[PDB]
Each structure stands twice: as C-alpha cells, then as structure tokens.
Image (cartoon, coloured by chain):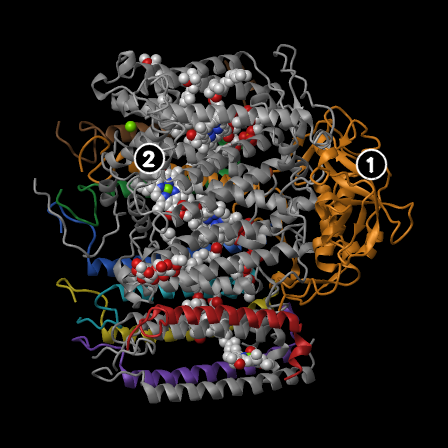
Chain colours: B yellow, F red, G brown, H cyan, J green, K purple, L blue, N orange
Amino acid sequence: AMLDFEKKYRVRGGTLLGGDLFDFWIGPFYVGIFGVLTAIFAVLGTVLIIYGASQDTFNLWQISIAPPDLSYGLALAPMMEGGLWQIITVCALGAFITWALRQAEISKKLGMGYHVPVAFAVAILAYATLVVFRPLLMGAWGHGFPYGILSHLDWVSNVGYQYLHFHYNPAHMLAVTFFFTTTLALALHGGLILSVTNPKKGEPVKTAEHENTFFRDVIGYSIGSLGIHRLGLFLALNAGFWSAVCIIISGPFWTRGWPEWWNWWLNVPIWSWG
Amino acid sequence: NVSDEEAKEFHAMFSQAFTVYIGVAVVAHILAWAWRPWIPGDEGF
Amino acid sequence: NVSDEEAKEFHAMFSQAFTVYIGVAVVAHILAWAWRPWIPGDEGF
Amino acid sequence: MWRLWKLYDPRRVLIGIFSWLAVLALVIHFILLSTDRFNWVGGAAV
Amino acid sequence: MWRLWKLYDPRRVLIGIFSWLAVLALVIHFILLSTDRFNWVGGAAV
Amino acid sequence: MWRLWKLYDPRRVLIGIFSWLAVLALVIHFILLSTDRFNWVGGAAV
Amino acid sequence: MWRLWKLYDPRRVLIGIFSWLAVLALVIHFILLSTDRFNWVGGAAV
Amino acid sequence: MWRMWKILDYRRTVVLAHVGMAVLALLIHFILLSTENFNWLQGNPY
Amino acid sequence: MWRMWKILDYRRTVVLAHVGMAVLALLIHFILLSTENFNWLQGNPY
Amino acid sequence: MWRMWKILDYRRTVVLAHVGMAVLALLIHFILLSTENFNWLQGNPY
Amino acid sequence: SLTGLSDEEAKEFHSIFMQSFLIFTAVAVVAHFLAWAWRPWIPGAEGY
Amino acid sequence: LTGLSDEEAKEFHSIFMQSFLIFTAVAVVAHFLAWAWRPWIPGAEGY
Amino acid sequence: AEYQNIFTRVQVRGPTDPGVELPAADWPRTKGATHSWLLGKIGDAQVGPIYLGTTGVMSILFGIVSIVIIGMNMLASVDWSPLEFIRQFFWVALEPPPPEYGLSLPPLNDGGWWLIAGFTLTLSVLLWFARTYNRARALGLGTHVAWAFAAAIFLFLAIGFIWPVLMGSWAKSVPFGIFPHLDWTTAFSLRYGNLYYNPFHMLSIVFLFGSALLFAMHGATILAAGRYNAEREIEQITDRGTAAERSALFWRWTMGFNATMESIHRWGYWFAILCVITGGIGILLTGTVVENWYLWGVHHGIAPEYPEFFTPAVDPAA
Amino acid sequence: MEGTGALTDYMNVAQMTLYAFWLFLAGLIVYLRMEDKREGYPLQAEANENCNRTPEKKLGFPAPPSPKVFKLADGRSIQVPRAEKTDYELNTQLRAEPTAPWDGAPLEPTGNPMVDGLGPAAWAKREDEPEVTHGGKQKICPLRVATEFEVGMSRDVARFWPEIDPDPRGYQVLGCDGKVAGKIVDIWVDRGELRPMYLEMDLSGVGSSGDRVLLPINFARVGYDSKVRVNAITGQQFTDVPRLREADRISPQEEDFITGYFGGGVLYAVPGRTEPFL
Ligand code: BCL
Ligand code: BCL
Ligand code: BCL
Ligand SMILES: CC[C@H]1c2cc3[nH]c4c(c3C)C(=O)[C@H](C(=O)OC)c4c3nc(cc4[nH]c(cc(n2)[C@@H]1C)c(C(C)=O)c4C)[C@@H](C)[C@@H]3CCC(=O)OC/C=C(/C)CCC[C@H](C)CCC[C@H](C)CCCC(C)C
Ligand SMILES: CC[C@H]1c2cc3[nH]c4c(c3C)C(=O)[C@H](C(=O)OC)c4c3nc(cc4[nH]c(cc(n2)[C@@H]1C)c(C(C)=O)c4C)[C@@H](C)[C@@H]3CCC(=O)OC/C=C(\C)CCC[C@H](C)CCC[C@H](C)CCCC(C)C
Ligand SMILES: COC(C)(C)C/C=C/C(C)=C/C=C/C(C)=C/C=C/C(C)=C/C=C\C=C(C)\C=C\C=C(C)\C=C\C=C(C)\C=C\CC(C)(C)OC
Ligand SMILES: [Fe+3]
Ligand SMILES: [Mg+2]
C-alpha cells in the first residue's frame, strides 16, 4: 500500500550498488542493496545477541554481551569471552553504515540532498568512537561498551568515574550544552509551528510574519524558518561530534581527573593574583 | 473479492503446506519426547 | 527482458570465474589440511 | 504448489530466502563456535 | 603609507586598535597584579 | 574476459580495486605489526 | 444549571470528568495501599 | 476453512506466517539452549 | 543453470558477490587468527 | 440510557473500553501477583 | 496474475526451484551425516 | 469486505463463534491437563 | 558539487520589520532594530526590536536582582578580587543553606542570600512564562511555546524547590555556580545510589536523546528538501507541496512510517517536554519514595549480575 | 521491602508511577501516529498488491483521525487531507510503466520524466492563487516590484568584500555540463521569509534572450567568479523549465512545477545518474 500521493515518486534509479536487482519496495520500505545488507547485518546481530542472552539470562534489562578482557588486546576473542561482542560490533557497524548508504539511495531517488545520511554519519561516528576508535587508541577492544540495556549504564558510570568527576571534561560540558540547547531549540521550534498552525480556536492560521514577530517579541531575535533547521541540525550534530570528542580524549589524551585539567585556567598569568 | 475457486486454490496450497509442517512438527516432538520428556514430575526430571 | 543468448553469455563468464575461484580454493584447503587438519579427534589435535 | 509464484515474484523470494540462509548458516556456525564441544577450530576433546 | 587609509576604513581601524589597546593594557595591568614583584597595590618587598 | 569492461565503467572498477588494495594492504601490515614475530620495527626475536 | 451544557460540549465534559474520576480513584486506592491501616491486600492487623 | 481467504489476504498472511514462525521457532530453540536439561549442545545430564 | 541471470541482473550480482565474499573471507581469516592452533602468525604448537 | 451513544461514538468507546479493561485486568492481576497472600503462582501460606 | 508470470513460467520456475532446493538440502543431509560421524549432537541420558 | 451485509455479518458471526468455541475448547482441555500436572490454586497452607 | 543549504549565499535586505500589530493596550515595542550580515548567513538577519511589557519588565527586574545577589556573593567569596573572580569563575557559587536549618529562613550569609536568589529567580522565570504566554496570545498564536517552557520550569522547580521542600531542608537544593551545580548533580547520584537506575531518569534520557535525534532528523530533512521550499513549513501544512511529500516519503521508505509537516513538530514538541517532565518526576521520586536506586533496581530485577573477576572486598565495620 | 513508598510486599510508588507513565506514553504514541496520518491517508492499495486483484484502502494502525479544518487568513476553511489534492493524485495518469507487475516494482518513465512529473521531477497539486503576506502584499515577488529590498545584507560587506555578500544580477548561468544557459536578470524574494527564492534568468545562451525562466536558489551555486553553476540540469535543459503564467507573480503550484523540474534533473538530466556506481 502507498500514500495517495506516493505512486508517482516510486521510480527507478538512485542506487549506489545493486542497480535494478534490489531496487524495489517491500510494503512501505524501500529495499535496495543496502537494505538487504542492513537486514542481514541487523538480524545476524540481533539473533547473536539473543544467543548470548540465552547463555546468562533472558531478563531483558540484564541481557549483556560484554567486550573481551583487556588482556586480549586487539586479538579476536573466544565467542563466550567477548568474541560474540566483537562479531555483534562488526554486524552493528555494517548495519549502521548500510543504513546510511540506503538512506543515500532514498535521498537521490526523491531528489533530496544527502543531509540525512551525513547527519546519521555523525551518530555512527560517535558509536565508532565508542567501540572502535577509542578502544584502538587505548589498545584493546575490551574498552568498548557492553551490549546490554542496563550493563552499558554501568560502563558509562565507571568510565565516567575513571576520571573522578566527568562533569569537568571540557568537551563533555560542550556536548551537554549542545544537547540541552538542541532540545530547548526543539521545544521552541515544535511549539512555534504548532502555535501558528493551531492558534486559539476561532483564529486563522497565521504566517511566518507571526513566527518572526513572536521571537522578536520574546527574546529580541528570530532565526527564521530556514535558520531554525540549520541551527537545529547544527546543535544536534555538534552534540554528537563533541560527544565523540569528549570520549575519545578520556583516556587516550587524558588519564588524570578531569577537574585537574582546569589547572591551566587557574594558572593563567593574567589572573593568578599570587 | 476473491472468487470461491481462487480461495479454494489458496486453501489447497495452504492445506498441503499445513499438513507437511504439522506432520514434521508432530514427528519432531515425538522424537524430542523419546529423548528427554519436558514435563517434570513432582521430583523433577 | 534479458534474452537466452545474453543470459548464456553471462553464465559463460560466471562458469569460467567460478571454476577458477573454486579450483584455487580447493588447492588452498588441501594445503591447509596438509598443514594442520581442522577436524579435532576424540583428544583434539 | 506451482501457483505460489503467481503470488510472489521469483526475484524477491529468492533474495529473501538467500538472506535467510546466509543469516541462518552464520548463526548456526557461530553458535557451534561458542560451544566447547563443536568448536572445531578450538579443538576441544570429548 | 597615507594610502593605507584609502584601503582600510578609518573607523574600523581605529575601533580595532582601540579594542586591542584596551584589552592589551587590561591584560598587562592584570598580569602585573598577578605577580608578586609588580603588584603595586599588594605592597610586597623585593 | 575483456567483455567485463563492456559491463562496468573501467574508472569505477579501478577506484574499487585500488580501494580494496589500499585498505587490505594497511590492515595486513598493521596485523603484522601487532604480532610479536612479524613486527619488524619492534625488533622481535625468534 | 442546565445552561452549563450550552457552554461546554457535553462529550468533552463527560470525557474530562471520567478521566478525573479514573485518575482520582487510582490515586486514592494506591494511597490506601501505601498505608498500614487501609491495605486490604496486605492484610495488616489494626 | 477456505472462506478464511475471503477475509484475510492470502499472500500477506503467508508472509506473516513465515516471519512470525521464524521468530517463534528461533525463540523456542533459544529457550531450550538456555536450559540445562535441553541444551543439546552442552549435553548436560538429564 | 544459465536461467538464474534472467531473474538476477548479472552485472549487479557480480559486484555483490565480490563485496560479500570479501567480508566472508576476512571473517574466516580473522576467526582463524583468533584460534590457538590456526593462528599462523603466532605459531603455537599443534 | 441508550442515548449515551448519541454523545460518544459507540465504535470508538467499544474499542477504548477493551483496551482500557485490558490494562485494568492486567494491572489488578499484577497487583495480586505482587502480594504474598494472593500470589497464586508462588502459593504462599495465607 | 500478480508478478505477471504465465502458468507455464510458474511451473518452470517451480521445477528449477524444487531442484535447487533438493540439491541444496541433499548436500546439507550429507554434511550432517559427516558432522554426526564426527561428534553426535544428541546427548545420552548421562550427557556427553 | 468493509461494508458487509446482514447475511454476511450473520455468516461471519457464526464462524467467529465456532472458531472461538474451538479455541476455547482446546484451551480448556489444555488447562485440564495443566491442572493434572501442577495445580495453581494453593490451599491456606500453600503448596 | 551541489549547494548544501548550510549558509545563505545571496541575502536581500529591506526595511526593518516592525512586527505584526499588537492590540491597542500593549506597550510599544522598542525602536531599535538593525540587520546583521553574520546572522543573515544562518537565517533571519534582523536583530530586534523587542517587546517589554509588565511581565517582561518585572521578570527582568526579578532576574537582575537574582543575578546581582549571586554575582555579589560570588565576588565576595573571593575577597572582591576581579582577577580571582576570573580565576575561580567556574568554581564560585552562592551556597544553599546548611542542613541544620531545614525549611526555615536561614541567615543571609548561611543560605539566606541563596534563598532570596532562588525566590527572585523563580519569580523571574514564572513572569517570563506569563510573557511567553501573552506574546503568543497577543499575536493570536497557540500557547505551545509557553507550556513547553512551563515543562522546563517544572523540572527547575522540582530540582530546586519542590524536592528540597519534600525532603524538609533547603540544603538538598542546588547552588548557583558552574562547577558547584555539577558537584550537586554528581553528589545527588552518589547519595541516592546511581540515578542511572532511576527509570524516569532513563525515560528522561530517552526523550533527551530522542530530541537530539529528532532535531537532527528533522533539521537534516528540511535542509535536504530545501530545494522544494521545505523550510516554509507553514505553507506545507496548509498546502502540501512536493517538499512535504518527499520528506514524508523519505522516512516512510526508510523506517516504514512517516509523519506530516505538522505531526513532526508534534513529535519534537512532546519529546522535548517529556524529557523535562520525566526528569522532574524522577527527581521527586528519589529521596521521597526511593532511597537507593541500585537497590530499587535489584528489587525489580534490572541490575546486571557480574561473574567473579576480583576478590570481593569485605566491609571491616560489618 | 519496607519504608515510605511501599504499596505491597513488592510494589512501590516509583514503580507504579512508572507504569502510569507507560500508559500515558502509549496514549501519546497512538495520538502522535494519528496526527501522522493526516497526509496521504487512507493508503491506496493497488490491485496488484491484493490477492483479489481489486484496489482497496488501508487505514493502518492507528487509523487516521477525522478531517481537520484549518481556518485561513483570507477567510477560507480548508479541510485536511485536502479533497482536491487526493482527487488529483488518484486520477492522474502517470506517463510511466512499472518495471514489473508485482507490488513494489519501481516505475520506469515512458516519455520525458522531467516534464511529466515522475519521481524527483514530481509536483504536488497546489493552489494557483499567488500567496500574500499578512498585510496583503505579494508574498513572492521579484525585486523589480519588491523595490523596498536591495541585494546585499551589509552595504560595507557588499562593497569591500563582495565575494561573501554577492549580487548575482548579471551573472552567467551554467548547467551541469558546463554550458552557458543565459544571464540572471532579476531576483525573486519572499516578503515574509526575507530571503531570495528564485533567480530569474533569460535564455540568451540556449534560446531567446527575451524569454524568462526561474531558477530556484537552492539549485543555484552562486560562485565567486560571476558564474552561477546549476548541477541539477544540463544547460540545454533550461529551455523546458516551466514558464510563469504571469511574468510578475508565481503561484504555489508554479513553485512546485519549477522546483520539481530542477529536482528531476538529479536523476534524468544526463544518462548514468539513474545508474548505480557499480
Ligand atoms: C558518571 C558518568 C558521567 C558521564 C560519563 C559519560 C561517558 C563514559 C559517556 C558519556 C557520554 C555523554 N554524556 Mg555523560 N556523564 C555524566 C553525566 C551526564 C549528564 C548529566 C545529567 O549530568 C548529561 C546530560 C550527560 C551527557 C552526555 C552526552 C553528551 C553523551 C551521550 C550522548 C551521545 O554520545 O550521543 C551519541 C549517540 C550514539 C553513540 C548512539 C549511536 C547510534 C547508532 C549509530 C545507531 C543505533 C541504532 C539502534 C541500534 C537502532 C535500534 C533498533 C531499532 C530501534 C529497531 N552526561 C556523568 C558525570 N558520559 C558518552 C559520549 O559522549 O560518547 C560519544 C559517553 O561515552
Ligand atoms: C514450498 C514453497 C515455500 C513454502 C510454501 C508455503 C505455502 C503456500 C504455505 C506455507 C505455510 C507455512 N510454511 Mg512454508 N514454504 C516452504 C517451506 C517451509 C519450511 C522449510 C524449512 O522447508 C518451513 C519450516 C515452512 C513453514 C511454514 C509455516 C510458517 C506455515 C505452515 C504452518 C502454518 O500454517 O502457520 C500458522 C501460524 C500462524 C498463522 C501464526 C504464525 C505466528 C504468528 C505471527 C504469531 C507468533 C509470533 C511469535 C509468538 C513471535 C515470537 C515472540 C517474540 C520474542 C516477540 N515452510 C517453501 C520455502 N508455506 C502456510 C502458511 O503460510 O499458513 C498461513 C502456507 O499456506
Ligand atoms: C579480471 C577479472 C576480474 C574478475 C572477474 C569476474 C567475473 C566475470 C565473475 C567473477 C566472479 C567472482 N569473483 Mg572475480 N574477478 C577477478 C578476480 C577475482 C579474485 C582475485 C584475487 O583475483 C577473487 C578472490 C575473485 C572473486 C570472485 C568471486 C566472488 C566470484 C566467483 C565465486 C562465486 O561465484 O561467488 C558467488 C557466491 C556468493 C554470491 C555468496 C554470497 C555471499 C553473501 C553476500 C554472504 C553475506 C553475509 C555476510 C558475509 C555476513 C557478514 C557477517 C560478518 C561477521 C561480518 N575474483 C578479476 C579482478 N569475477 C563471478 C561472480 O561474482 O558471479 C556472481 C563472476 O561471474
Ligand atoms: C548525532 C545526533 C543524534 C542522532 C542522529 C541520527 N540518528 C539517526 C539518524 C540521525 C540523523 C538517522 O537518519 C537514523 C534514522 O533513520 O533514524 C530514524 C538514526 C537512527 N538512530 C537510531 C537510534 C539512536 N540514535 C541515538 C543518538 C543520536 N542519533 C544522536 C543523539 C541513540 C542513542 C543516543 O542511544 C539511539 C539508540 C535509530 C532509530 C536509527 C538508525 C537505525 C539503524 O541504524 O538501523 C540499522 C538496523 C538495525 C535494526 C540496528 C540494530 C542492528 C544491530 C546488529 C543490533 C544491535 C547492536 C547494538 C550495538 C545494540 C546496543 C544495545 C545496548 C546499548 C542496550
Ligand atoms: C523542553 C525543555 C527544554 C527547555 C524549553 C524551553 N526553555 C525556554 C523556553 C522553552 C520552551 C522558552 O520559551 C524560554 C525562552 O525565552 O526561550 C527562548 C526558555 C528559556 N530557557 C532559558 C534557559 C534555559 N533553558 C534550559 C533547558 C530547557 N529549556 C529544556 C532542555 C536550560 C538548561 C539546560 O539549564 C537553561 C539555562 C532562558 C534563556 C529562557 C527563559 C529566560 C527567563 O526566564 O529569563 C528570566 C529573566 C531573567 C533571567 C532576567 C535577567 C536577564 C537579563 C540579564 C536582563 C537584561 C536587562 C536589560 C534589558 C539589559 C541590561 C544591559 C544594558 C547595558 C543594556
Ligand atoms: C558582581 O556581579 C555583578 C553584579 C557585576 C554581575 C555579575 C553576575 C554574575 C557573574 C553572576 C553569575 C551567575 C552564575 C554563573 C550563576 C550560575 C547559576 C547556575 C549554574 C545555576 C544552576 C542551578 C540552580 C538552580 C537549579 C537553582 C534552583 C533554585 C530554586 C529553584 C529556588 C527556588 C526557591 C524558591 C521558589 C524560594 C522560595 C522562598 C519561599 C518564599 C518559599 O520561602 C519562604
Ligand atoms: Fe521544522
Ligand atoms: Mg557543592
């Protein structure tokens, strides 16, 4: 089934691989070659996760596929000692990368720019930082995070407290600022569009004049219809990127407590006062 | 909608697959029961 | 759309490449088995 | 039972069947690599 | 060098110079206050 | 086998093959470095 | 008092009052469960 | 019960039957591999 | 079976075959490097 | 009281009543399962 | 019909499909016979 | 199918009630077997 | 080589937009409005004018009083040194009352200044809420922005007022400092046993991460469909252009389901405000009805169990 | 357990608060998915998707809400989903043939997909009345009538660093194949959005110098060397860009015609764009 306007858009072309062979839709999903791959990768990784779950516990929150011991270095591990995690990592990476390449096939077919696959490549960059880049720099795949709903929260807790106060990480304070600011911007953007198209009952749908006037009335500046989506993309992508920066520098480029990092600020010759 | 003849051809294909699938399932469970019965007694297995 | 002639030409190139790839791969496994067989015995290797 | 192909395009069922076989073969081969008895390259004893 | 002002707008050059001079004199005065030897109001001895 | 180049743009094949060679060669060298026998710069002994 | 229903939509007020009644009943029942004296499932002795 | 196909589309039902029984059968086989008496790969005593 | 190419486009299948078999070949080689008895670089006794 | 269906949709209310009573039936059973005097699966002394 | 296959095309694809399926299954049957001779996978009552 | 008539609604209803009766009947037997295995209503002492 | 809709290449400047006419009781807007080339690259170039009414002025006055109290106490803590103020800028704070005062009014230098700063800050944000509400109503807009702001207010009040009041001490509240309120955030989690196991903190993060996910998805989609004037989203809601169809088709083909030009902003609006609402509820639950969140997670079977890797420590004081 | 918050031997207040939020989150998710189904619904199941070989309508789950009335500024209560757009889409005879009869097969255009509105070249059915501002001015108008706008946000930047504050008037336009299509004569601005939207050009390079054509700004890459490079379409293809009904106004429909035509170039402008990398 299709949206009542969808038929005319379902044309041939836009693929990067596979050509006509996979260029079709199953229900609403466009398939493409990267959809077949993202399906094989996703099913493989999910079924491997459930196998790992069957060996410890089926409780959804307590399922955990953990990375190997640090003593393994970069070697591939036995399956039940983190080798299962490593296969799931290469399956998830492939699932993410083929998902973005597939969104690139969908982008070209609808004549859209590649903003969505690239914006997703930032999210893939952050996961790659967590499971590939940072474990590489530190020298062991065991530095990646476990695949479990509650077991990866203990990883975040302990890795954060490896630096004794992770709030003082300068790149983390920047990434948190970008995360808080982008949901603030999302609240304003979503709210303002709803406020115009859904005014008080008995009022006409308003214009982009009212949108600019509203924020110029409130804060004295309005970024506009186009600016809100550039800034919205900018804030969320910087949120992802500075997440990657904050974690890649935690351990490969800083092994002490993050509060100590601010010792350079306390020592600036301008304001030492002693 | 489908006619009776189309729907009967659907159900002929379904009944063929259903019988093979259930027949293999019945045999498989009879083998699994001969191997290790899965209903515990009052004292376990 | 593809005719039987152009299909057979595609299968012709498939067969030449498949047999060369399969042939060299068979040699690879015979050398690998001559080196260290990968089917463990009752005591392993 | 030939009429199943009056319903499903041969290209799509073959793509789905082969994708299913690829997932299945890897999962079973990997599950055996997880076990101590069937990890053939690991080569445990019985 | 009189032609320098046919290229660069005098107001922007003077604003740029004034901003640099204000920041620089503030930074030098602050750096001196941060040192033990040149803190003139801290009243230390040499 | 010359018919193969009737099927693909030779430029896209040269890009594809040289991309495999570049990544494969780096990985093989890096794996050899990671060993304690074929790490040539580490001065491993045998 | 009947003119209340020419001011507000009867369905809307019915939906809102029932939602308030459902929430209040849930809140009170669990308020009693959290106390010692009025926990009927807990079977606490007074 | 061929009148079932006068209600439910036979194609979409068959696809749904294969995907659902796939996940169900994986689920049950995994449940047995989680146990100690039916994990045929571990081969524990019964 | 030359008829297989009247369903699957041959040009695209060849490309998919190479990328897929590259992944599988790397996967198998990496699996052997993980094992003790078939890590040819580490060379543990057999 | 049949005039109730001239205010709220009968089609909508029937469906939301099944969903609403689904949650309520699930909630009460789960509340009893969270006790000790009424957990029939545990079968604690009463 | 859906998929636009004539009845003869459906019957011809069926025979090749069923042939390819029996050949694929037969090799699996042989591989399982070899796998069973190596290490049986149905434990006895006392385990392995 | 959406606009079923009276005779088609009566015909669907009878088949629905027959399917539900068979589904319930098989389940009832399943519960009679499950009770024979392990009863699930404890006495005051427990199990 | 395609234009990426990241910076506006060609800009056009006209007269300053004075805004839509207000009702004939509102204060006059300010007269100050200028155009910025730098801001015009990202979006609208006009800066100002701004409205200021009763609620706006009183919010600013209450907020300035709060900022002066915090700033002067911050400056006083470093012996009034502006240099030492810059050196310690992230570390200084207006400290909340010590625990011994409970909910009473403590002396100025023992949390009294904190309580006044918290009161005036609360008043300014509440008046700012009324300002956002009235500016929308004055233009005939819905009050969605104000209620989304009210949702952020509730977490702010839950953290600083309601939860400390429910706990019976102003000490539990958060100091006005940069690193100190980060110290409060960490200590809060330490005290009540790993806020990670708080489910409403989990949900809060779900909607926070989903908000960044949504804005990234939506912002990228509007820029990608900018070739079809997607960013003119109001026109697409009332008159579905091809951009609205390509945006919906893109996500329908990707993940199997889509939104509309209007429903995407409902998804993002609810994700933004649910993040801050589950946040407030999670804060109100801890300390009051959950003592230790890890022990709560153990009770409800959500804590992972870890095999032996080390010799477990034993409390000598057991 | 015991303490404040206990509701039973196992249930506590935080847990039941959580399930209370689960019920709300579901009702919100269902509500949000219904708001999702006000454009393009009900789904059009074609005959070749269903075993009965009859076209149908699928509501999906949750089913779409009732129609929604947007009262408009000019005094026109429009209903969503709009009847005229649905009626246009269901009746339009596409100039394309499915590459296969089964459901999900892509359409292959028969004639010229760019002028026929196929795929990335497609347009929606929109209003033919040109948009107005809140005050009644013409919303999208060229700078010759919208004379209160001058090109360039900053006069000093436009005068001393014109590279970053350009004025594309008089610029040469090149297509994806590098050929010269003509000269930019005017810029169209949105009085509400305060942005350029279209670059009107003449066809002095590939057609009549007196002909006028609109180039959407997001398809134009205004360079630093007085050349505007359009990657969407070949220079020869600028001649078939749809013309305005009136030389000084554009309806929302013509915006979808013009942006649609350029978007279609992404696949159909030159051979090989449809074809994969490999
Ligand atoms: C005690 C521990 C420390 C701490 C230790 C850490 C550590 C360690 C980390 C963070 C990271 C983060 N911290 Mg911290 N952090 C602390 C307290 C906080 C507080 C707070 C309330 O005080 C906040 C707001 C934050 C905020 C943040 C973010 C900036 C960042 C996580 C976002 C991110 O990485 O996106 C990136 C998003 C992803 C990586 C998701 C990947 C998406 C992929 C590509 C697709 C997946 C698809 C999926 C499988 C689909 C599912 C299937 C379908 C649904 C069917 N932290 C405390 C002080 N923090 C993380 C970070 O920055 O890493 C990059 C990180 O590693
Ligand atoms: C020969 C050509 C095709 C083929 C042609 C056909 C045709 C024609 C038919 C089938 C049908 C079936 N085929 Mg077949 N089938 C083939 C070969 C196989 C093989 C095999 C390995 O050889 C297997 C195992 C199967 C299996 C099946 C079954 C799914 C089904 C018969 C049982 C049934 O009636 O389902 C009944 C079960 C249901 C209706 C419900 C299924 C499960 C639902 C969705 C709910 C369970 C979900 C589950 C609980 C989720 C798990 C929990 C998660 C953790 C959340 N087929 C080949 C590949 N097959 C029949 C069918 O599809 O019936 C409708 C049918 O008509
Ligand atoms: C000058 C000529 C060209 C060339 C011309 C041709 C032509 C013509 C053909 C080939 C074909 C092949 N070529 Mg060649 N080929 C060249 C030289 C090579 C060299 C080499 C080192 O010299 C190699 C190794 C190969 C390799 C191959 C094979 C892929 C293939 C033959 C076997 C087959 O039929 O696969 C088929 C097997 C499959 C398709 C299995 C599919 C595997 C799927 C994708 C598995 C996916 C699951 C995934 C791995 C999961 C990952 C999980 C992990 C944990 C990460 N070619 C040169 C460069 N080659 C043939 C071919 O590709 O036909 C299709 C063919 O017709
Ligand atoms: C970088 C800015 C933010 C962002 C952006 C972003 N995310 C995106 C996109 C964009 C632009 C998409 O276009 C893409 C999309 O299409 O979303 C609908 C996506 C997406 N972001 C998603 C999730 C997601 N994003 C997150 C974060 C973020 N995404 C950032 C905050 C998170 C977090 C913070 O946890 C999650 C969970 C998906 C909904 C979707 C990508 C879907 C995808 O890749 O599907 C591939 C196939 C699968 C079924 C995935 C599973 C396959 C694996 C083999 C199994 C699972 C392995 C995994 C390691 C398990 C880990 C579990 C434990 C951590 C519990
Ligand atoms: C959905 C939840 C998210 C959210 C939403 C949200 N926030 C909001 C809103 C919304 C919907 C608003 O409408 C409102 C707003 O104004 O948005 C622009 C706001 C807002 N969120 C803000 C901050 C904020 N939001 C945050 C978070 C969040 N906001 C959540 C993540 C945070 C974080 C992460 O901690 C912060 C810090 C404000 C910028 C703004 C409300 C401002 C406010 O209440 O101000 C009160 C008044 C004062 C502080 C007075 C002092 C201000 C000046 C110093 C006065 C100047 C005096 C004079 C005019 C000039 C003097 C100088 C002379 C030399 C000229
Ligand atoms: C000297 O400085 C001058 C004057 C030059 C100006 C400079 C000012 C500066 C630099 C100020 C710097 C300020 C900074 C950096 C502040 C940092 C603030 C931060 C990070 C705050 C973060 C969190 C604080 C919170 C959440 C506070 C919450 C407090 C609340 C919600 C208080 C509520 C209190 C109420 C409602 C009071 C009730 C009083 C009643 C009446 C109930 O008592 C009986
Ligand atoms: Fe938007
Ligand atoms: Mg502190």
Above or below, B7 against A186 in this view is below
Which secondary structure lies at badge 1? loop
Q: Is residue M25 left or right of residue N241?
A: left
The x, y position of residue F2, in whole percent, is 66, 83
Identify the residue at horizontal 69%, vertical 63% (top origin): N274
The x, y position of residue A66, in whole percent, is 31, 58
Residue N267: image quadrant is bottom right
In the picture, which quadrant includes the C terminus of chain N?
bottom right
The Cα–Cα distance between marks 2 and 1, rounded to whole angstroms, is 58 Å
Q: Is residue N114 visible?
A: yes
The x, y position of residue H37, in whole percent, is 21, 68
Which secondary structure lies at badge 2? helix
Q: Quadrant of ligand 6?
A: top left
Above or below, K39 against N200 in this view is below
- Both marks 2 and 1 on one chain: yes
Residue where numbered disc 1 is placed: N249
Q: Nearer the viewer, residue A263 or L4?
A: A263
Q: Is residue A259 left or right of residue M191?
A: right
Q: Chain of mark 2?
A: N
Q: Nearer the viewer, residue M24 or M57?
A: M57
The x, y position of residue A36, in whole percent, is 52, 65
Q: Chain of mark 1?
A: N
Type of the residue with mark 2 = Thr
Identify the residue at horizontal 58%, vertical 30% (top origin): A192
Residue where numbered disc 2 is placed: N17
Q: Earlier in the sequence, mark 2 or mark 1?
A: 2
Label 1: few (<14), some (14–19) or many (≥20) C-alpha neighbours in 10 Å: some
Identify the residue at horizontal 82%, vertical 36% (top origin): N249
Label 2: few (<14), some (14–19) or many (≥20) C-alpha neighbours in 10 Å: some
Residue M263: image quadrant is top right
